[PDB]
Each structure stands twice: as structure tokens, then as C-alpha cells.
Amino acid sequence: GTGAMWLTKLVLNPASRAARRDLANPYEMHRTLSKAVSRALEEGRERLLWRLEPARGLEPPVVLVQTLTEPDWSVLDEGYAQVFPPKPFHPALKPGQRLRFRLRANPAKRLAATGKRVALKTPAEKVAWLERRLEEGGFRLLEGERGPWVQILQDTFLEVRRKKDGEEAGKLLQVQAVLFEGRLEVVDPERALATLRRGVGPGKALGLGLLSVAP
RNA sequence: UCCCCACGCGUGUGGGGAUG
């Protein structure tokens, strides 16, 4: 019960306009990153996930990219990013294992009244959403004295211009992006692996949903 | 929360959102 996927670390170059474009617009980032696994996506063998990492200093922006298939970063423009070699990742997941995690996700609900997806409003609801999704996904958010072992380090409403070739009007993608960090435990290694590989919650094409775990 | 899909228990649930 090991599992496999590929992780790539990209260190983006603020001097590059293409990098700045993608850092500011998760949908454009989606378009850039997709090229690295273009044929796998078309063959229906791929689920690309990524996260723009929180910066804690003046360091350059770091983007973590997970793919099910081996990525080809030769597609990146010269100067766009420094690319660390994609590396096969075999997550160690066994029942009861405690792990630190980071997840930028879209805690949302589809309103009965409007049929539309909207953001859950309060921190309590965002945390409950995470607890629910983690448990359904074979993990479990740790609960220590002082509450759930999670912190919400960022909570922002994204309004992102979206445009595909052949489309006359460019739509506006609007999604709430919540950055969670904390501690969880593995419950069911197989379901937990599927959750790492498939991602958690909406907006996966927009740099949300990548559950990253580590001892 | 702008669009699309799946659905028989949820604040409706889940999935999708390149070919510049």
C-alpha cells in the first residue's frame, strides 16, 4: 500500500511576464502547467494539481505541481522558472500515522435555493468542511485540547478572468481560496492515497485541492 | 460563484473548468 505520483517544484521568476501572468491568474497557470502533461490529459490518464506555496520571506514564488504521469517541463518558456527534476513520490500511508498537511481548498456549498456553488462563510464552517472531506477521503483531522489541529492561514476571494481560444466572451471565475495547515492521521491507506492523487474539493484546475502531507 | 456534468438523505453532495 505505497502509491505513486510525480512531484515537481517550480521556482518562478518574477522578472518573467509569463510567470507574473500565471501567479496572478490561476486559470492562466492551469493553461501553462497543462502543457507539461498535455498528452496524458488528452488520453484521460491525468489529474494535474498544484499549489502556489505561501511565502514566509522575500524568496521567489514556489509552485508545487503534482501529476499522475511523468511531466515534461521543456514546455516552459526560457526564464519562466527554475525547474527541479520531477520526482516519483511514494507516500507512506498506514493506519494511525500522524502527518502534517497543507491544503489550499475551496470550502463551498451548492445552494438549494440558487443551484450555485458559494463559499461557506465562517471559519467554523470552513473547518467543518475540511473535517468532513478529510474523513470521507480516508484521513482524519486531529483534534487536540484547544480544538482541531488546523489553522486557516489565508482566506481570499479569487476573481479570475477566464478565456479559451474560440470563446467570444471571457467569463469570470469566482472562487473562495482557503489555505489550511495542520495535523491529520491516516485512517484508510487506500482511500487516503486516492485523496492525495485526486485532490480535495472544487477548483482543482485553479491551484486548489492539492493535499500535501509529510511526517 | 461565471459555466458544464452526475445524483435517492448533507448548509444539497460530488466531479469538470488548457491546446495560449
Image: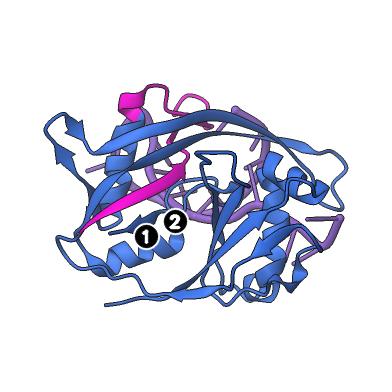
Chain colours: A blue, B purple
Q: Residue at x 69, y 70 (%)?
A: A73
Number of residues whose C-alpha sits closer than 10 Å to that of mark 2, classed few (under 14), some (14–19) or many (20 or more): many
- Tell me if I can see residue A110 in this picture: no
Q: Is residue A80 above or below residue A177?
A: below
**Outermost residue, front direction?**
A58
Q: Amino acid at mark 1?
A: Thr
Per the rendering, the mark at residue A199 is 2
Q: Residues at badges 1 and 2 in contact (C-beta under 8 Å)?
A: yes
- Compared across the picture, whether A199 is left or right of A11 comes to left
At which x and y percent is residue B8? 33, 47
How far across and down, in percent of the image, does residue A41 sit? 63, 70
Residue A106 in the image: x percent, y percent?
A: 47, 39
Instruction: Give the amino acid type for the residue marked by disc 2 in the picture.
Output: Gly
Q: Is residue A124 above or below residue B3?
A: above
Name which residue lies at 18% across and 31% down. A147
Residue positioned 50% across, 74% down in the render: A87
